[PDB]
């Protein structure tokens, strides 16, 4: 809206919007990546629990 | 030879990218789920023993 | 190209108005009335009951999954207790979706159902349709929920879905505030807001104003202008532009917005996209949205002329004169319209803007009388249009078809078809808003 009524146009006037659109893309990329870290943590916890159950079953069997 | 410049005087259409209101992306799927081949193997050993080697 | 029926009529002077920007000249025919294209529709006879989805969030041990379709519990699965490690596949989301689809196929052979990335899609034959679509899982719907084309809240949409799926939000179910459609995009994995099913778009691309564009070779082309179609919502949520029913009287450009004057409605385009008169998206009122404001006052005012300026936009009616201005940016909420004067304006006047002054003709019984209106920025100082041809009320025949003039040589030419052999000069000179010279004369060429 502002770059449309300016009466200037050009390359710098498009760099203003391009940089802004980039900030939103990077911020969303962070939401999409914070999720990946959380899923990785859940994965590690699940593997740890499974390994603990495995070791406990070995202990029970060994008597 | 000459070039039309009205589209430059305006926002020339279909050039790079146009955005609407796209929402609800949801990112991606997951890399499978925590696999338990180790525990399945161990429990198979346990049952095999508890059935055949535990008379 | 594209025909030439737009330029017709035995009186082009009184039926054609156009304004030119670099390399385009938009032409609007006052007699032609815009219409909506009934042939163009997204989904002509869409049946929202044709298909559905079954989002599978996950599996919990010891629960039971039931799919109820058309009164039949087609699918029934009992997840094991969970003592054996082999139950990992049984609780897996994709394995469970495949099992549910297999059971549905066994209990519904004719129906076609295919497994998705995180869902089961049910597509009934054309003859039949889905009436009842409910699922019971015993875990407060945290494992699987039924998804149809009507989803209450935005978050209810499944994370993944077929590429062409369409869903309507209808957030309130009793108000029109939150009604819009979103379709999934497989490749991008994003739900994109799009125009609803069985909804028209485009305005036939013919009755709308055309343009005269200079081609690359240096010649000129006459064609319609590619307008933008509706991008979201049905007719109840994205109403047609007010010009779609009536004709367009004038074409102008204010603040970089292609504007039209249809009936009592002033219609402006987007800040930069001149061919897009519809808003962007119904999610949050945007800044560069089109303006379709209607003047509301005691008298139904038919807008006739609109001479623009750098920051003001004079709007003239038969017995009204408004000024559409906005402090800052014209954003459809900061737009302010204020009545200024109430002098009479005739139908066939041809205003010409020489700087602030705008000269318009007011025909009389036999001889026209020119008028001048100043465009002072201070609305509190506005004065009714003057009559420069007061000492010479005659001397101009009743029919005037051009009031073109210059601003650097300080003159205003007037042409009349009553005596087409004469050009009427009006030489003036203003020193600090002071009338120094007034000269009236004609140039008789034979």
Image (spheres, grey):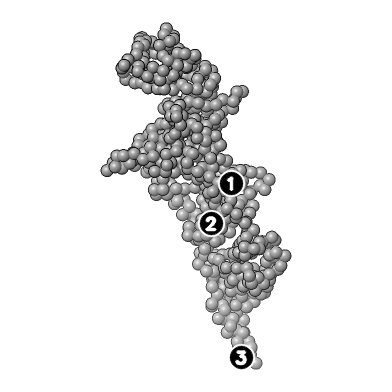
In this view of the protein, which residue sits in the foreground, C419 or C116? C419
Pointer 2: residues within 10 angstroms few (<14), some, or many (20+)? Answer: many
Q: Is residue C412 visible?
A: no
Q: Quadrant of the C terminus of chain C?
A: top left
| Mark 2 vs mark 1, CA separation in Å | 18 Å
Residue C261 — which label? Answer: none
Measured from the top left, where is residue A29 in percent x and y? 46, 54
User: In front: mark 3 or mark 1?
Assistant: 1
Residue that protrudes farthest toward the left in the picture: B1
| Mark 2 vs mark 3, CA separation in Å | 56 Å
Instruction: Say which element carries label 1.
Output: loop
Q: Earlier in the sequence, mark 2 or mark 1?
A: 2
Residue B53 — which label? Answer: 3
Residue hosting label 2: C184
User: Please, is residue B4 above or below residue C400 in the view?
Assistant: below
State the residue at coordinates (41%, 31%): C19
């Amino acid at each position: 809206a502002a770059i449309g009524e300016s009466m200037l146009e050009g390359s710098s006037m498009d760099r203003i919007k391009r940089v802004t659109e980039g900030q939103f893309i990077r911020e969303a990329n962070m939401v999409t990546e914070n999720y990946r870290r959380d899923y990785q943590a859940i994965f590690a916890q699940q593997l740890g629990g499974t390994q603990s159950a495995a070791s406990q079953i070995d202990e029970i069997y060994k008597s | 030879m000459s070039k039309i410049e009205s589209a430059l005087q305006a926002a020339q259409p279909g050039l790079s990218r146009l955005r609407g209101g796209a929402g609800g992306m949801g990112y991606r799927a997951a890399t499978t789920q925590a696999e338990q081949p180790r525990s399945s193997l161990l429990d198979t050993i346990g049952r095999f023993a508890k059935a055949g080697a535990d008379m | 190209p594209n025909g030439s029926n737009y330029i017709k009529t035995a009186n082009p002077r009184n039926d054609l108005r156009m304004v030119t920007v670099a390399d385009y000249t938009f032409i609007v025919n006052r007699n032609v009335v815009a219409q909506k294209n009934t042939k163009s529709v997204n989904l002509p006879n869409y049946n929202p009951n044709q298909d559905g989805l079954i989002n599978v969030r996950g599996g919990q041990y010891g629960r039971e999954l039931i799919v109820h379709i058309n009164g039949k519990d087609v699918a029934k699965y009992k997840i094991p207790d969970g003592s054996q490690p082999e139950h990992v596949n049984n609780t897996d989301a994709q394995w469970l979706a495949e099992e549910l689809a297999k059971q549905m196929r066994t209990n519904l052979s004719d129906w076609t159902v295919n497994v998705g990335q995180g869902f089961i899609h049910v597509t009934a034959p054309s003859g039949q349709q889905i009436d009842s679509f409910t699922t019971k899982d015993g875990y407060a719907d945290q494992l699987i929920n039924p998804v149809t084309h009507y989803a209450q809240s935005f978050s209810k949409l499944p994370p993944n879905a077929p590429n062409g799926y369409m869903v309507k939000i209808v957030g309130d179910a009793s108000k029109s505030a939150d009604q819009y459609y979103v379709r999934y995009d497989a490749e991008r994995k994003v739900w994109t807001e799009t125009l609803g099913w069985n909804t028209e778009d485009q305005v036939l691309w013919e009755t709308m104003p055309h343009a005269l564009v200079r081609a690359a070779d240096g010649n000129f082309d006459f064609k319609w202008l590619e307008w933008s179609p509706k991008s979201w919502g049905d007719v109840d949520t994205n109403p047609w532009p007010s010009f779609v029913g009536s004709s367009i009287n004038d074409v102008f450009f204010f603040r970089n917005r292609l504007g039209f004057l249809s009936g009592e409605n002033i219609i402006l385009s987007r800040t930069a996209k001149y061919f897009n008169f519809y808003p962007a998206s119904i999610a949050n009122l945007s800044d560069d949205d089109p303006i379709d404001v209607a003047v509301s006052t005691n008298r139904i005012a038919i807008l006739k002329y609109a001479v623009p300026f750098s920051e003001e936009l004079l709007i003239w009616s038969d017995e009204a004169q408004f000024v559409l201005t906005a402090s800052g940016t014209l954003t459809s909420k900061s737009v302010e319209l204020n009545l200024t004067t109430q002098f009479d304006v005739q139908d066939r006047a041809r205003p010409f803007g020489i700087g602030r002054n705008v000269y318009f003709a007011s025909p009389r019984s036999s001889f026209t009388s020119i008028h001048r209106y100043y465009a002072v920025q201070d609305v509190s100082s506005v004065k009714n249009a003057e009559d420069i041809t007061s000492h010479v009320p005659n001397y101009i025949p009743n029919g005037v078809f051009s009031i073109c003039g210059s601003g650097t040589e300080n003159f205003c030419s007037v042409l009349s078809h009553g005596d087409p052999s004469k050009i009427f000069m009006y030489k003036f000179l203003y020193l600090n808003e002071e009338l120094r010279q007034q000269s009236w004369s004609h140039w008789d060429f034979g």
